[PDB]
Length: 115
Image (tube, rainbow, N blue to C red):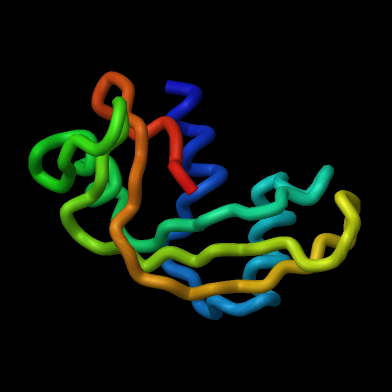
């Protein structure tokens, strides 16, 4: 698993078209993160197998206490809440970045994104 499933719902979108403010506003609503508005949330893009592989030597290294960092870089879109209210409509500003990602793994599956 349930935590791996939750990780995908909250943090994975394979192939976005736009990666702009409108995208953030749409996907945050679709993934159930707007009641109340989540303040910051990252979405990782690309192939699911590469993300799972962070949990193995194939695409990851030990990081800090009990986390793992990816060897490869990923396209990641950060959505940051704008305005002063916790309640909809939730307005977001998007950053379309590219970087290594840090996760915690359990039984070989990512279950938490650091962020």
